[PDB]
Picture 1 (cartoon, rainbow, N blue to C red):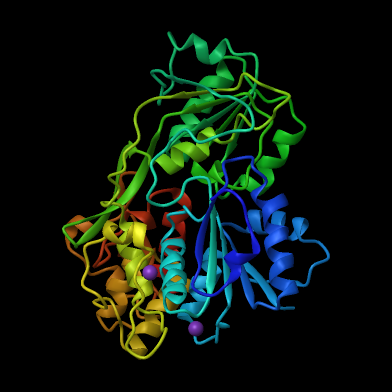
Picture 2: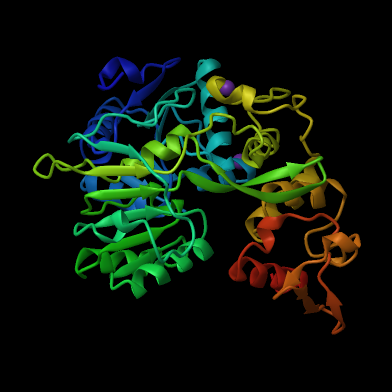
Length: 432
Ligand SMILES: [K+]
Ligand SMILES: [K+]
């Protein structure tokens, strides 16, 4: 459905509001849902994908009794909701759950959808999932406010000299999606040397660098998938490699960052969605480098979502299932990741304070290791040695001895970039 009506708020209803990019999902639909929830005294939670998007929502709901957190309407990020479900905090049994960008495949988002849909199925609440690409659908070219010219081309993924003149010959403004900051740096450097003005966006530099797009005379924005949500540009072109790095669990033993491999239809729709937004500016184009793949069962996030869900309580003995259209994404035995009370607290602390990936936290917690015991960071097999500048990374441990970083369980997400590695060295040293 692409239109909200009051009947959608009755218990037992789960509605997916297909709102194409630029439809006014935040500014138009949401306040109408919220005012009807407030009017009828439904205890409601609104779930935003990011803190950036949550701020936009606060603005669109100015004046309404809404309590933002990290009143009878609460607003929080998908991750905050799921984390609160895992903590001792007593989370209200909301009558209504509103999830924005409900296609988001972060483990906490997947788990939240499973918890919510289960509560609806149990007859305890209603839910509204808002997204341009409903889970279970595979249309990379949804509707837009203005027609988009879609052209498949050879998109460069490394610095280039010759060819790809269509890239530089463009006099408009382009948003370019790349799989990593590294890949972006090379592409930006190449573009800067060709005389173009480039601003690079990434999770850690967004808040500060996004501002520059609003006033500077930029030609290109080289960004990672963080611009898939909560980022509006005044652009007429999107270049999309249609690739990303995905964490994959190899032989239930380690997590690698595989790829770059094809993105999903929903990611491709969101990227394309950055353009075709302005009726008064037709002619926007989306230039893409390959096909999409629905086969993302190798993505670790699905299993990670199950690990989280198995540790969220609903009713004595009951284990929440994943949202039905996503349930087949994971091969797992129900409740197999349910941890007893103490190991569960360790798991939670490892993800929250420790900031470890869900899969890694689970391995450490299930082995009976306590939060602050970091010996496991140094006693793995030789092939788990972590490198810094292609040489073994080393850390001064809490007792002053310099040890080689060699964790018992290897998860590539802890050393994928300099910031991640720096953070994991701090963890190994007991500084967190
Ligand atoms: K809780
Ligand atoms: K479910």
